[PDB]
Image 1 (cartoon, helix red, strand yellow):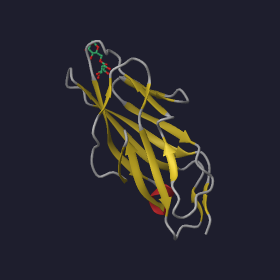
Image 2 (cartoon, protein in one colour):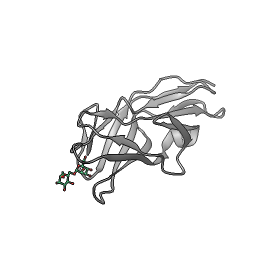
Image 3 (cartoon, helix red, strand yellow):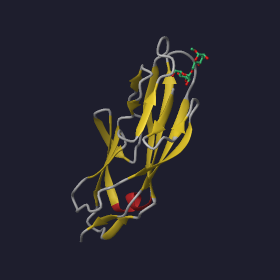
Length: 158
Ligand SMILES: CO[C@H]1O[C@H](CO[C@H]2O[C@H](CO)[C@@H](O)[C@H](O)[C@@H]2O)[C@@H](O)[C@H](O)[C@@H]1O
């Protein structure tokens, strides 16, 4: 089991960490969702599907910077939604093919009324999402840590 980003950055067997830089809607109004879809950005596969089945959860999700201070919202994982930042581990997703498959995570963040101007700064860390991988074969329990950075400023009109 291993993963990589759309940019080619890999986290190999056994886990590790990587940086993910994402483009964001440049203007978001109060009450409107800023969508951060990582399913187009993070992909993983199973390295021996002939015998092994891999199980993958969103172990933890944390907020930082302008997201921590200026937004509230949710994370959607494989079709179900939970409060973000997270308070518990999600149910698992099955990986059973060598063909790369999206990690089905997306953030839905809405600006608070009191925010004004630039709510997220270009190049700043906005979130850390931890992928946890186990299997039905041995005692492997590996974590893949994705550090999510903003490519551009996000503006909230007051
Ligand atoms: C067939 O067993 C051989 O390969 C196993 C490879 O283990 C990696 O891939 C598994 C399937 O994606 C994943 O579950 C595991 O955590 C590793 O990422 C290895 O464990 C066996 O020991 C043997 O080498």
